[PDB]
Image (tube, helix red, strand yellow):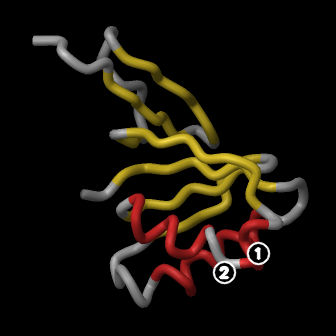
Amino acid sequence: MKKHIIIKTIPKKEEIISRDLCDCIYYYDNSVICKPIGPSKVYVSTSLENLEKCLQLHYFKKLVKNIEIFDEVHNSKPNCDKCLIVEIGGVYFVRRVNGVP
């Protein structure tokens, strides 16, 4: 299942990391999307397993500090309350709280 992942990178390398991660993941998932999204942050949409196959290569291990996994992305303010909403670019990432009816 696709997730909406924010990767924290070292400073100044967002654009190259986005480009190179998309060229690595394409083999596993021809539908991947990547973009640089803020200072020290890259967006990727793919399954977590496909991301990790690439993030464990030597080249990416050096450049990536952490990741944050979200369930949804919206271009307008989301309407949920029982959730975490993070705005990066002018894009809204949502992580839902489990067990809400």
**Kind of residue at disc 2:** Asp
**Residue displayed at 51% across by 61% down:** 44
Quarter of the figure with the N terminus = bottom left
Examine the image and state in which quarter residue 86 appears. Answer: top right
Residue 49, x across and y down, in percent: 40, 65
- Residue hosting label 1: 16
**Residue displayed at 46% across by 36% down:** 93
Regarding mark 1 in the picture, which secondary structure is present there?
helix
User: How many marks on residues?
Assistant: 2
Q: Is residue 67 left or right of residue 12?
A: left
Q: Is residue 89 left or right of residue 25?
A: right
Residue 55, x across and y down, in percent: 61, 68
Farthest bottom residue? 27
Near-viewer residue (101 or 76) = 101
- Residue hosting label 2: 20
Res. 99 mark = none
Q: Is residue 2 left or right of residue 77?
A: left
Examine the image and state in which quarter residue 77 appears. Answer: top left
Examine the image and state in which quarter residue 63 appears. Answer: bottom right
**Kind of residue at disc 1:** Ile
Do tag 1 and tag 2 residues touch (Cβ < 8 Å)? yes
Quarter of the figure with the C terminus = top left
Q: Is residue 56 above or below residue 67?
A: below
